[PDB]
Length: 137
Length: 137
Ligand code: HEM
Ligand code: HEM
Image 1 (spheres, chains in turn cyan, brown):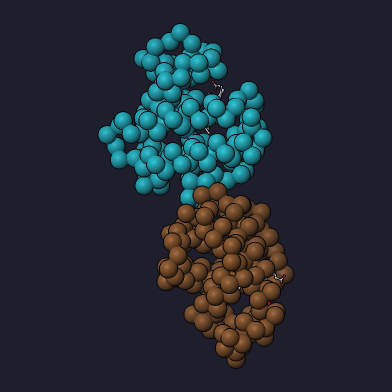
Image 2 (cartoon, chains in turn brown, red; image 1 turned 135 degrees about the vertical axis):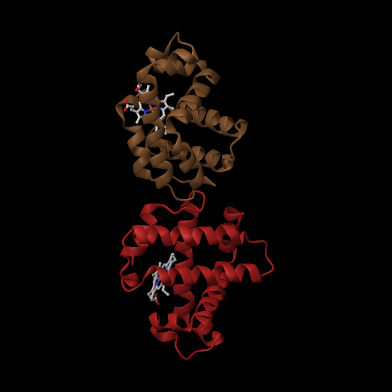
């Protein structure tokens, strides 16, 4: 289920983080604009970039922490606030977060693994509602 | 579902509040110790006590608001905080609340209405979880 999924992703965090983030960037090309050093690079080129692996891993590490702290897939208000006031997110709207989770859910469904995709869909929706109440447009 | 259940209970609150609270007290006789004037009385006698109906209704008026304010059966941290800080609850532990929901879920399953008993069970567990986080033993 949801808790096992967190253990699965953490077990090979580097791999899952890179593949899911690329799935996100290629599904929503407009999103790459927020990350100027990823522009004009193929998937393999990015997988070779030290900063790419490190950053994506850090993004997913925090996502897993938030997911582990949640109750019945509902994130803590404090975690939502933390994501909203991070300077790196100053610019962002809930729309950007919805797209990430759509790509994440689609990735899980398309993989071979037995992820609890329904819970992740729920988690993403609840997280987006939480960002909204936290003041994100 | 859960949201419709809130509307159903609100539509005949006094009746539902008394029957469920009576179900609670009769399943757990020991819990009546927290309510001084309820010992040694039959159900019909309690229902004729103005104080019994007035307080049970107020208890359910608030319970429905907490449920209404919840996201995915997960109550707001602030509502959990209010329940723990209420002076009338200074001597309670999460066990008392757990028993109340066991009785409430049993009541719904035994009735003939189409209540979403599974959701109320989840709500009860998540609320107990929230009470513990708010400092309740
Ligand atoms: C709830 C999901 C998300 C989490 C947990 C998260 C987490 C993080 C973290 C921890 C960092 C700092 C990285 C470091 O330490 O170097 C970061 C940076 C950043 N995030 Fe997020 N993020 C999320 C969603 C998003 C979304 C949806 C966007 C926009 C499509 C976004 C855009 C950025 C950008 C532009 C940076 C700075 C760029 C960089 O580090 O190269 N993030 N994020
Ligand atoms: C989350 C479920 C609960 C809610 C929303 C709730 C709500 C309330 C409210 C609003 C009052 C004040 C009523 C007034 O104005 O007189 C009250 C009083 C009280 N509650 Fe609770 N309560 C809950 C659970 C419990 C439990 C599980 C117990 C322990 C069996 C309990 C014991 C009491 C007592 C002893 C009083 C004061 C005695 C009395 O009013 O006659 N409550 N509660």
